[PDB]
Amino acid sequence: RAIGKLPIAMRALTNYQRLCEAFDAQGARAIWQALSHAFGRRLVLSSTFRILADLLGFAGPLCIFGIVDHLGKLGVYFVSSQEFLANAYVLAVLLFLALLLQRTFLQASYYVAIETGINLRGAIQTKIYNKIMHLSTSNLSMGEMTAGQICNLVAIDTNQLMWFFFLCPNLWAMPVQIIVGVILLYYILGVSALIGAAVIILLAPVQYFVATKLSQAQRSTLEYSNERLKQTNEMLRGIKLLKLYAWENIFRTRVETTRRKEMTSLRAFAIYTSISIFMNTAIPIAAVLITFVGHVSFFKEADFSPSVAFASLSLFHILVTPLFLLSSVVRSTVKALVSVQKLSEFLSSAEIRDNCCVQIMGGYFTWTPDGIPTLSNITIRIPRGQLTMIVGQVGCGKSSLLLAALGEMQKVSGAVFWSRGPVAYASQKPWLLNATVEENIIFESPFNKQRYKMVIEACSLQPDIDILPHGDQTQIGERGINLSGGQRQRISVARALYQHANVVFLDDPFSALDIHLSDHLMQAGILELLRDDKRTVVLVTHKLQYLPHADWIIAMKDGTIQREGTLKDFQRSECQLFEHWKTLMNRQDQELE
Amino acid sequence: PWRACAKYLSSAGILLLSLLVFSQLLKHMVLVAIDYWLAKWTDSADQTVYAMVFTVLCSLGIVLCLVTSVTVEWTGLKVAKRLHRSLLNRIILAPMRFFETTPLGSILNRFSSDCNTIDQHIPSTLECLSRSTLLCVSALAVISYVTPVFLVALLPLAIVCYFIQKYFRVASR
Amino acid sequence: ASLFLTAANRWLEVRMEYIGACVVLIAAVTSISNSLHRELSAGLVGLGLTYALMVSNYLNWMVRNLADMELQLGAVKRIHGLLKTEAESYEGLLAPSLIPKNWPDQGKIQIQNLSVRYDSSLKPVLKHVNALIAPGQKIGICGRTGSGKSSFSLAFFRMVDTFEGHIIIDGIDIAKLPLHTLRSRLSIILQDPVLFSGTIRFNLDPERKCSDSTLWEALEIAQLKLVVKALPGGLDAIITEGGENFSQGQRQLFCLARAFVRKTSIFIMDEATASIDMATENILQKVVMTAFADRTVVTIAHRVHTILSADLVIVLKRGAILEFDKPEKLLSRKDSVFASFVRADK
Ligand SMILES: Nc1ncnc2c1ncn2[C@@H]1O[C@H](COP(=O)(O)OP(=O)(O)OP(=O)(O)O)[C@@H](O)[C@H]1O
Ligand SMILES: Nc1ncnc2c1ncn2[C@@H]1O[C@H](COP(=O)(O)OP(=O)(O)O)[C@@H](O)[C@H]1O
Ligand SMILES: [Mg+2]
Ligand SMILES: [Mg+2]
């Protein structure tokens, strides 16, 4: 607070609107043409300040050539220009007025480049959020990328593209610095100046050679560090099971072979950057060697003065001083090229295309773009406002039927007729927003205090909220305190008993809960707050004793459904699975009514 | 000076830490000596004795640039090889109460960003820092020898430089 | 905040470059006034001009690289802060020659006066408990949530703060043991399923030290053999990150198949049957009680009809043994906590 908000020209959704407006100007070349169409107007402004700087930094060598050649050496009033520009005090105060303007224009040209890098960071973070809100879950689950790679992309590759845009107008000054320094060297020494030719051709073949060898270091370096961060993430997530099985030496030697395999590419990278900075800082001292022995040998002596010697020494130093940054420039642009190729690989990924609520009717749902359909030919007549149980064995479709009605799956055939609306859904693995416990339960609803005190008392969060050091205000989740899992499943299903959304997709709440707390879920909350108002609750569980409390039972086996209907309908038609449920519950004497 | 640069100098070792300082200050003082030899060679009015030792004194500056460059890459690569391979074997032998009370994103944060910073982002900043401040202090060693009038002006500018450094440094931190 | 850090850093390098231009003015004026009305022969004056321009070029890089060296040495301060942490003190007081080569031969798990915590400051979550376990005694443990059930399975591996006690298996003290020898040969299976990305052969056996017949018979006694053989890999196929290629019951079933490759004597379980259905759950209890006759199998109960056919049943309410008796004896007493737990189920 009191730094205040940023203005309107640097907002996200002012830029990113310019970035999607550059997208409809019709790979990675579309992203580069969109960035050169979007942010190039201020990039040429920072290059305009960059080229208006360091031609005013070329008053150093002309000033030294002025005053050392001075210091070795209407008609009574006025002073001509050759008498004006050959005196040391007036040229030294012109040297003071040159360095203030070039060293203000350098710090303006840094600021416009860093400000457009910050607006690039805001626009590409909003475009990465608009990609991740339309991403299918088969990108994360079946194969291709990880969650750590997606949050590693914004943490690294966005900052690598931003740090390339911090040094973007320095690459466009690297023509105009060397060319005007060569013509200002040609003014001073003439034809003896061009046999300081280690600079003036650069051997830019060998600079492009060490640039492509830094590419051969850099792509294997980013691939091995993504593999090592993936292995370290699964090791530190599973360190409880790895310490209990004593497999920490085996997984540590896997991470250590990944670290040594990365480290050999780091050996190649540090040796190639070392010979780049050796070539970079040993070319201009060799250039003053071959121009200063080559002035007094091989060429007949045209006025080897201290003025032209210190002018050529300061001119090679001002010629060499932006050239010192070039190894960091070429590693930043190869990190940009690997960054924008991993960015263009991400945004072109797979995406999302009368008594009843959902009418899945003949729908083939598939987890895979190329595989066989996991969910088979199914026909579902889930009713309004009633408790409905999906039951079955392991791997029959009991979570995929819930994810099919959200539209997460790949719908091959059939049609789903909703009412899509809001839907209360607590998943199989639970989910914790990293905030206070009340803010995980509220989940951006209005704060209903009596309903919030009701759903704590519906599913017994009061003795496990009394044990917390701040109660409602405890920071649970990844950042902050660790819960048990029995409180995590209960804290995930307590937010899907709250959010007014009238279709409740309760996946399995009775893994981590016991018999008494599962019945306290089953008496109050379920059957007393979800059937209080007319809210459709679709409660898939393996706890088969609650199938008495069931207005609709869907049976699941091997990707297809057997039958839908009530429990007297399952008594009438099927009877084999009814006798199987009579044997599994050990209720042979009484009846499932 | 914090404790982290002390842990950086102990993890690099004294056998490369002695080669770090005693290549670079010798290279910058022979850069001062070849520019002083360029000053004294222009004071001509002895033939080629201010050319031949200028040639061998430039080629020793070239190979001193080479040993400074291989020393700075071998210190950065050795501290990449040694710091990780110690944090991993020290953090895998933790108790389970240490994993229970910490955020997991902190332990993944110190294996990703700080191991990214220690490997490749530190030694370019170290070679630019050592080259830039050693070029600056050898340039201030050049202008004391030419002019002794500069030393009565040097102290108020260094005083307002240190005052603007402290007065910036609290706000920047 | 990054634009404010930017504009503050450009403010610092503006004033430092202006001080360096004042150095160029003062050194230029004193080098021409030190050589006009004196004799300094102009090569030293051009030397002072070139190195004054070197001051103006390389002062801002010095303060920028010093502030960047402070900000990048904060990462070394964070890793040095993590690096002096607590170790678990892995080596025990016993010599490793005095433990047998076949250490888990038969399970005489003696418990006397155990009470655990998790650290020094907390409350004891286990009260003073004692039991004597035979090697053919396939016990089970019931209770409420938070009553010490998973902490009782974690106390066999010294994972919790067992600050006292007589937890001795086979006449050899478990506190006087090397921890790799302890947590190698005994195998727990947790409630929350943790799988690792890669292949199925690695995710059961990371050493690749057991045979493919042992992995296929461990998938036989889990009942996941017809699931994995109908997969297009067959074996050596991809499990992704978190085990999210498969179901949660398949993730618990791969935890069972990882538990069954290392042979045992002291199979201890948590409530591994949480996400599994009752049909394949009552299939899998009928296999591994019969496939493992001699091995002592301890299991925390989630369904008490699974636990009902054990040898003895421990009941843990609020960290103490309330009951340690026959299941038909605790059923026929008809007021017991085991009888009310099986009454509230079915
Ligand atoms: N995220 C996924 N990506 C690809 N395939 C999946 C995924 N989840 C499940 N499958 C496949 O779909 C089948 C059905 O699994 P589903 O998602 O319905 O879990 P489930 O059967 O409800 O789990 P449980 O029975 O333990 O509650 C499984 O056999 C599995 O092979
Ligand atoms: N990391 C921990 N630190 C302190 N106490 C814990 C920790 N984990 C679990 N406990 C305590 O152990 C008790 C028993 O929990 P547990 O054995 O996991 O399940 P159950 O409640 O089914 O017995 C809980 O009441 C809890 O307070
Ligand atoms: Mg499921
Ligand atoms: Mg437990």
Image: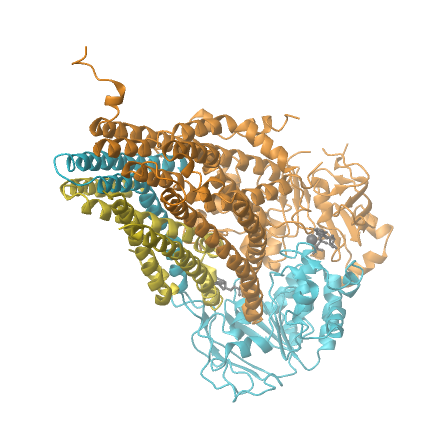
Tell me the quadrant of the picture where the N terminus of chain A can be found.
Answer: top left
Query: Left or right: B107 with respect to C69?
Result: right
Chain coloured orange in this rendering: A
x and y, in percent, of residue C20 in the image: 26, 37
Q: Total of numbered circles in the picture?
A: 0
Chain coloured cyan in this rendering: C
x and y, in percent, of residue A468 in the image: 44, 54
At 57% from the left and 65% from the top, the residue drawn is A257
* Residue C32 visible to an observer of this rendering: yes
The furthest residue to the bottom: C98
Above or below, A541 relative to A387: below
Above or below, A409 relative to C131: above
Query: Left or right: A15 with respect to A372?
Result: left
x and y, in percent, of residue C40 in the image: 17, 41
Above or below, A159 relative to C205: above
The furthest residue to the front: A300
When asked about the image quadrant of residue C123, the answer is bottom left
Above or below, C6 relative to C307: above
Give the drawing colour for chain B: yellow
Tell which of C146 and B66 is nearer to you.
B66
x and y, in percent, of residue C192 in the image: 60, 60
Tell which of A211 and C43 is nearer to you.
C43
When asked about the image quadrant of residue C307, the answer is bottom right
Query: Left or right: A542 with respect to C62?
Result: right
The furthest residue to the top: A74
* Residue A14 visible to an observer of this rendering: no
Tell which of A262 and A3 is nearer to you.
A262
Type of colouring: by chain
